[PDB]
Amino acid sequence: HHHHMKRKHIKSLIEKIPTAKPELFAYPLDWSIVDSILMERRIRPWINKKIIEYIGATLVDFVCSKVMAHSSPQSILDDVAMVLDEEAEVFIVKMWRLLIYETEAKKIGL
């Protein structure tokens, strides 16, 4: 189950993720699965790793807290655009694809 459920349903979970930004931003994200654990396990490091490509520190925690505050994807994007231009728009799209995939995967266990 460690990462076993994520790999086994690759065909199914990927179908859930919308390819259009407005549709994907509208996606009914279950924040109840977005808990304290999922942040340290997969989300927080993913953010910190992806931030290196754009810049080469303190901002990392800001983004985490906003996801934990269950903010609108567009609301965060606006705040990040103050730091990372139009690269910030590509940033959240890819993160939302992550959240959907993760949140959805822990539901597959039943």
Image: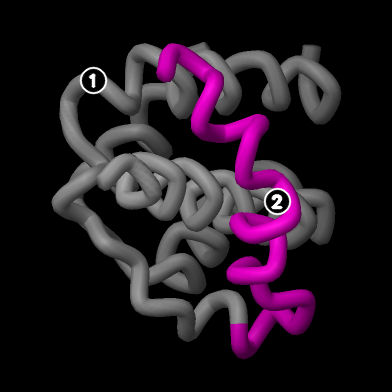
How would you rate the neighbour count of disc 2 (Cα within 10 Å): few for under 14, some for 14-19, many for 20 or more? Answer: few
Q: Disc number at residue 37?
A: 1
Q: Position of residue 22 (x, y in %)?
A: 63, 88
Disc 1 marks a residue whose amino acid type is Ile
Q: Position of residue 49 (x, y in %)?
A: 67, 15
- SS state under label 2: helix
Q: Disc number at residue 94?
A: 2
**Residue 24 belongs to magenta span:** no
State whether residue 55 appears in this view: yes
**Which segment is the magenta one?**
1-23
**Residue 8 belongs to magenta span:** yes
Q: Is residue 65 above or below residue 47?
A: below
Please tell me which residue lies in front, 4 or 91.
4
- Please tell me which of labels 2 and 1 falls first in the chain: 1
Q: Position of residue 37 (x, y in %)?
A: 23, 20
Q: Nearer the viewer, mark 2 or mark 1?
A: 1
Q: Is residue 34 above or below residue 26?
A: above
State whether residue 81 appears in this view: no
Whether residue 78 sits left or right of residue 10 in the image: it is: left
Please tell me which residue lies in front, 83 or 88.
88
Q: Residue at x 60, y 70 (%)?
A: 16
- SS state under label 1: helix
Disc 2 marks a residue whose amino acid type is Lys
Q: Residue at x 36, y 24 (%)?
A: 61
Q: Is residue 101 above or below residue 45?
A: below
